[PDB]
Length: 109
Image (cartoon, rainbow, N blue to C red; front, side, top):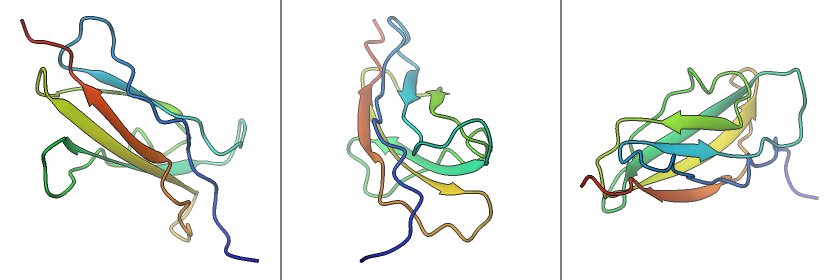
């Protein structure tokens, strides 16, 4: 009745590794697909107060991931992530965004 799209890489969480005020582990749940077919992901990051978005390029996230330990984040400040997935090639008629996930890099002191 509508379109064709490889379903959101949903359940996007920013779970922090206890003490690590430099790192958030961004975890998500791939469409449904199992132990084959390469999925390519656009994970864009930035600070809570930024106008436009930065990037985690589809390199790590160029073959079906479901998790990524994001490193080099400013302490105590909220860094926010936005992801969607396409199936192998460039033909990918995008799945409507997984969601926004917003993570605070604990405290420096």
